[PDB]
Image (cartoon, coloured by chain):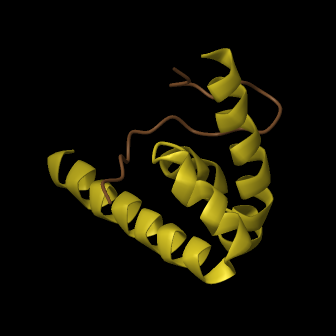
Chain colours: A brown, B yellow
Amino acid sequence: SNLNPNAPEFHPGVPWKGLQ
Amino acid sequence: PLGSQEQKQMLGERLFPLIQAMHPTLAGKITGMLLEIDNSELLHMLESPESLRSKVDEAVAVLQAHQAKEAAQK
């Protein structure tokens, strides 16, 4: 239920940041 | 490990077109916030368009609330 506004943006075709 | 990382990437690849159709301007940000939650809810959101709408509407309000806090500073 907790959403982070500072979450990394998702862009198709490029690896998502904050990927663990 | 790297398998779960590919699972998180592909879930974003499935969610992005649906969110871009819903909220095209801020689709990239909503997908990034929704990708932080557990994968079990993400697979459910792809099957139910109403559950995806509820999470997206909650995500857009989170960004709207944070923009007001950032605007109150400078």
Q: Nearer the viewer, residue B27 or B2?
A: B2
Residue B35 horizontal/vertical position (percent): 55, 45
Q: Is residue B11 visible?
A: yes
Q: Residue furthest left?
A: B73
Question: Left or right: B32 with respect to B3?
Answer: left
Q: Residue furthest bottom?
A: B50
Residue B26 horizontal/vertical position (percent): 60, 58
Question: Left or right: B51 with respect to B25?
Answer: left
Vertical comparison of B18 with A9: above or below: below
Quarter of the N terminus of chain A within the rendering: bottom left
Q: Residue at x 56, y 76 (%)?
A: B51
Number of marks present in the image shown: 0
Residue A12 sits in quarter = top right
Q: Residue at x 48, y 47 (%)?
A: B38
Q: Residue at x 70, y 45 (%)?
A: B12
Question: Left or right: B38 with respect to A13?
Answer: left
